[PDB]
Image: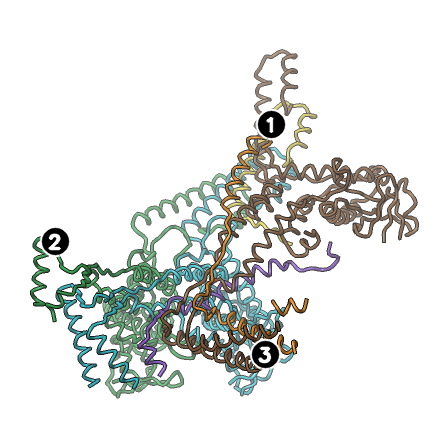
Chain colours: A orange, B brown, C yellow, D cyan, E green, F purple
Amino acid sequence: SSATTSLSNLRNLNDSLSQELARLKSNLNNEGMFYTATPSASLEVIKYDLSYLKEALALIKAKIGADTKEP
Amino acid sequence: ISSLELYKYSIFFRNYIENVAEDCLKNGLILESAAHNVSEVELARLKVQLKNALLNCIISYRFHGIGYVLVKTKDTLIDLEQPVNIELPIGFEYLDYEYVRDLGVDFDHITYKAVKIHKSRLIIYENFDYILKRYVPCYTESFLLDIYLFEKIYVEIERRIENHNFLFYKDESLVQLQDALSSATTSLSALTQSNNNHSKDISNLRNLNDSLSQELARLKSNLNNEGMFYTATPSASLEVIKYDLSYLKEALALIKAKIGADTKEPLTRSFNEQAKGLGNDGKGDRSNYYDFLKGVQEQVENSCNLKLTKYFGLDMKFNSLIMLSEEQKVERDIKLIELYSKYNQLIQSSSFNNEELAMLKEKLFSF
Amino acid sequence: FNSLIMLSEEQKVERDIKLIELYSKYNQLIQSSSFNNEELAMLKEKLFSF
Amino acid sequence: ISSLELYKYSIFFRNYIENVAEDCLKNGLILESAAHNVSEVELARLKVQLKNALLNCIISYRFHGIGYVLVKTKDTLIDLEQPVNIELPIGFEYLDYEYVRDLGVDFDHITYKAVKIHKSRLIIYENFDYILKRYVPCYTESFLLDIYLFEKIYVEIERRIENHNFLFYKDESLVQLQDALSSATTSLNLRNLNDSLSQELARLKSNLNNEGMFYTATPSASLEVIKYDLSYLKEALALIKAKIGADTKEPLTRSFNEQAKGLGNDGKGDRSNYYDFLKGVQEQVENSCNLKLTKYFGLDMKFNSLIMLSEEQKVERDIKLIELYSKYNQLIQSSSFNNEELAMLKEKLFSF
Amino acid sequence: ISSLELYKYSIFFRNYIENVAEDCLKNGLILESAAHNVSEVELARLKVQLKNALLNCIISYRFHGIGYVLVKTKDTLIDLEQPVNIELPIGFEYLDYEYVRDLGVDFDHITYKAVKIHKSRLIIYENFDYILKRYVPCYTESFLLDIYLFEKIYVEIERRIENHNFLFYKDESLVQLQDLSQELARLKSNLNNEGMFYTATPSASLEVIKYDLSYLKEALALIKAKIGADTKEPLTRSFNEQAKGLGNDGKGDRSNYYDFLKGVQEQVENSCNLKLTKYFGLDMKFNSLIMLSEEQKVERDIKLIELYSKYNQLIQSSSFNNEELAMLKEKLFSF
Amino acid sequence: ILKRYVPCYTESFLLDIYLFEKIYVEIERRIENHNFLFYKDESLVQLQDA
């Protein structure tokens, strides 16, 4: 982020850093195993829900059926 | 959302567009000549070409909002501008919408690619909306959004299929010793960048990740060999990370409901699970698809006969949407013969007045 | 192309039986009716088989 | 995944390969001679040998993509190279695919083991895919993967059947003293510690068996049952069955021998997918055989009808036909229709 | 996995092997002589011995891949090497597979235990797989594994039946006694007496340890599915819950087991008649797999008589042309 | 509409077939190690690391 801020010597620095980051990420993603070294590291799946929209659709269908006579 | 892009990518949109035209021209046409001078073979060939043109005409009507069929006669390319009084057409050719320039109903000619063609030689099938004061297709932005979501569900499924389940491993081993030395070196190098053994840091990082790959290979090898994953660190952790699909399932249900609400084509609504509902049930309670097809057929007939009869002396008709089977025909004939026999018996064995019999005649449907 | 729907032997026999019954009913009506020639002709067109 | 290895290991693959051929030759063949000079007994023996050859021919067609049947005549081994104009075959012999070398359709001979055989004496049943421009078997890599997974499920079941449930025991007792000393000094008497540890473990096992109570001294001692699970394999079996049913049309293979072949008589023209597939295979085999049996040998072969009527069905059909004839006779006798109308009825009637 | 060991240990494998042979020879055989000179009693005795030999022949065919039946004639033990031109057999004797040495089809003799027997006196029923280029049995390694797992489930059940539930107890003064032990066992007996277990240590613990069987139940379900997929024998697939399906339903839609039995019977008939007719002048046939009951026979006779009556009525009360009647004759099945 | 010759299938249909196969591809990938043991111990690594 500091590199990108400065962009918005350094060439070799960024090349080495990018190489290492890319290889670490590629290994962890390819082996089907996410590895980390920090004892306090955390990984959680965040998920959305649709029950609100389903219930709203039911209520809206009921209201439309009540509000019109066209079958 | 681009209709052309959706048409290219999705076969569902293509089927939705083309099903109506295919159903309209499924049962065929009837072609007749007012003068009663054209032979039946030539007229049948003309009918075949007319059907071929009408399919693309209806497809263009649904996709763009207007469809053009050129009535080709025995004339030169420059003679298309001149009007036609009375002629027998040589054939019918559908004209591509993208190559047709029309300035409106106030003009009596179009430009095709720049050949000027008079409107008297063209069969025009247009969907003009008076509220919008413009020609519109059969679909809207909401329908396009529904189709796009229908495809995006499986796009996301493909995005997350490979790594739906994976392992999260936290280990403070020799590997973390290397990794933590690496992390401290990278942080210090970041400080220096913000501002020299950074090359030493780089060589570290490289060898450290080499050893990391070696150790991960060894761990996987042990897992495969003895089915047991062993670790040294008392704070080591191993957890299975899993994805979910309930969101996409519920979205599919809602999208199917929306599509069914937004279209009347039974195959599109039911995802090719329901029939077209164009059979004979012996009752006058016809289907919504039947009514829609009848309206489309009436509009097409009006559009064709507005100029086929006036300028070419030809009349076109659509075949009946409901086609009776042989057994149904035999049953209907049997019932009609029974009705006639009952009527004859009543007439022979009754003494009703002439006025009463006549009055019965009008109130009877068959007689 | 040959017809997509192929009838079985039993179906053919049943159809033949029904057609023969229809012809017998038509013959009985013609023999035992006193309808006018125009009415009989008009019945002929409105009948599918005849 | 190797098709030969899968064939050797799995009986399901073998049955899938052989069921189509067995069903095709279940009802038998009809053999005829154009000259009408061959006696029926010799022709029946020829038909038996032809069926025996055709079974292996179809099996090789499904497994490899091509099948070879040699039409053996009264000739020497060197005469096989020479073409045949008109002859009466002595028999039929299936040729193994691995011993046949064919350079393509542009050549009119093959090498068998190195005897040169002209193609006019050979019945060839090949599955050529024009998209792939090569001969292909009836199975693909996905189907092989499905079969492999089907077997691997029970492979894993056998792997984890014995220790599906076991005991995890933690104890900082004399036994942990023994094992800690062993650990330390082996990393660096000890065999006596070994013996004492085993003795105490066996003693505790004996106590457990005797009085149904496991007792321990350490306040931090723990005992937990470790258990395995099978829901993954159950769901995988369901998915694999669905995939197999989608990937093949053979009813026994799809239903795991739970459904019938569907080759009966229902009195309707709505035949089954397996019936259509078998009819197509039979037509291809008939074409392949008659391309050279009639031209070079004066023989014609036909397949028996896939649908075989029972005696009761035959009697019922005869009764219905007799009733139809009686109705037609009654109508003709008691009608006064015109000759043209009766004739027109004749064509529109199926039976008459 | 050893097929012989599995056969010895499991009755299910034995039944799977023997059911096909028993069903094939359930309805019996028909034996005839081309010369029409042999008396019926002697021929019936020959048929009985032939059935007895054929049962073991089919069993050996299924278990090993080949089965041998020796056709015993009025000859000496050394005359078995000599070929036979025309003779009337004295009997049939099944030959054990383990005592038969055959070098292949290119040879016309075998060694039995070392008596040399010509192949013209032997009925051979073999299952040769052209893909494998060898004789193979009716079972494979996967099927053997399925049977082994089927037995191992109850092996494990027996292993863990006795201690499915037990007590885990933690106490410090009690081990001060143990390391007295039998006296605390007697205190557990006092628990059994008074219905109340009492202890001293505030950190003493008592927990019931229990086992589970869901793994074995699911494995049994999967194994049953695999067996049903891997075999066609209805009893083996359904665990003796379904019938053989060899009845008469009045329809041509026969069963898979019927088709399999018909194929096996055809192969056996070919194998026998390849040498019974040529060398011995005898012909063998299998009885029909479907056997009609008396009521079914009466019903069929009634229907046939009705059909004949209808045909006679039509012929008497019709005025059809001779060509039309003839054409009806061919298109009628019965006439 | 496309002004070109097109087959009977589209990219979405190809994607559907590809996913249909990829499901069992993943099943094969994770069939062998669907259940395994995770064990943590310090003396046993005192043994193994040596």
- Which residue does the numbered mark 1 point to in the structure image? C31
In the depicted structure, whether residue E243 falls above or below residue F28: above
The foreground one among D124 and E150 is E150
The image shows residue B179, relative to residue A5, as above or below, that is: below
Q: Distance between the residues labelled 3 and 2?
A: 94 Å
Q: Disc 1 residue type? A: Gln
Q: What element carries label 1?
A: helix
Direction from residue B151 to residue F29 in the image, left or right: left
User: Residues under labels 2 and 1: Cα distance?
Assistant: 106 Å
Task: Residue at 52%, 39% (x, y): give it.
Answer: A58
Q: Label for residue E196?
A: 2
> What secondary structure is found at the residue carrying circle 2?
loop
Going 64% across and 68% down the picture, which residue do you hit?
A: A4
Q: Which chain carries label 1?
A: C
> Callout 2: 10 Å neighbours few (<14), some, many (20+)?
few
- Please, what is the three-letter code of the amino acid marked with disc 2? Met
Determine whether, in the image, residue E234 is placed left or right of residue D272. left
Local secondary structure at mark 3: helix
- Residue D45: x and y in percent read 45, 72
Question: Residue B173 location in percent, x, y?
Answer: 41, 75
Q: Is residue E308 visible?
A: yes
Look at mark 3 in the image and give the residue it sits on.
D119
* Front disc: 3 or 1: 3
Q: Quadrant of the N terminus of chain E?
A: bottom left
